[PDB]
Amino acid sequence: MTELEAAMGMIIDVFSRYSGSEGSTQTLTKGELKVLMEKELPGFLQSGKDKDAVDKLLKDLDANGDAQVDFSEFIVFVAAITSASHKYFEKTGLK
Amino acid sequence: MTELEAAMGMIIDVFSRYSGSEGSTQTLTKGELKVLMEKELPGFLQSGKDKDAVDKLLKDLDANGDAQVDFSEFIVFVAAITSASHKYFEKTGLK
Image 1 (cartoon, chains in turn purple, orange):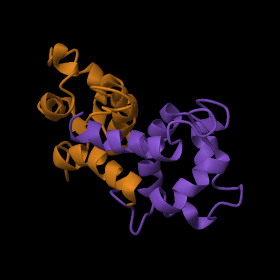
Image 2 (cartoon, one colour):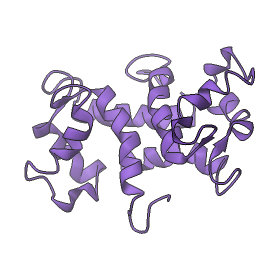
Image 3 (cartoon, chains in turn brown, cyan):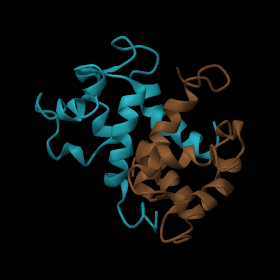
Image 4 (cartoon, chains in turn orange, yellow):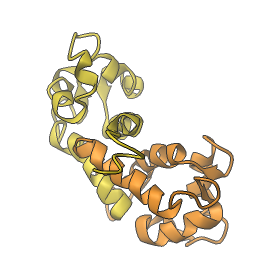
């Protein structure tokens, strides 16, 4: 757990706040994932939830499970979420 | 940026330090990378450099650019290094 590894430590932690330990099984279901989004995924809120984009913050990662997103699927796509927000955040976050 | 993306802030930050404006272009070249991993991947350093192992800590993310790793490519590999981060539990449950 260096600097990069500790940041992922807190993303695995975030997942361990909202999957909570278990909330489904030890995954974000689509119905859990939403309550996390308004807090830890601003900007992906362009739809805000409506089973449409909470569904895409699922469907992207969901490929690694089914639709109950494990910590693997989540942490892997938190490293995709960076590469989504940098397409245009306020400017192109980090370009 | 969010909490999740402030954490992404620090997993990208390692790349915002070394490649941290340009160094290569704005990629980890293999020759820049080799002094970072001593600091932010200490568990890879069981190999250490070898011009063929710093090269595999390249070739896994070099999928982008054959020896010039961009930010969004390092970051995918970093979200595999989350499975090395641990030290104690989900991450390190005792920090």
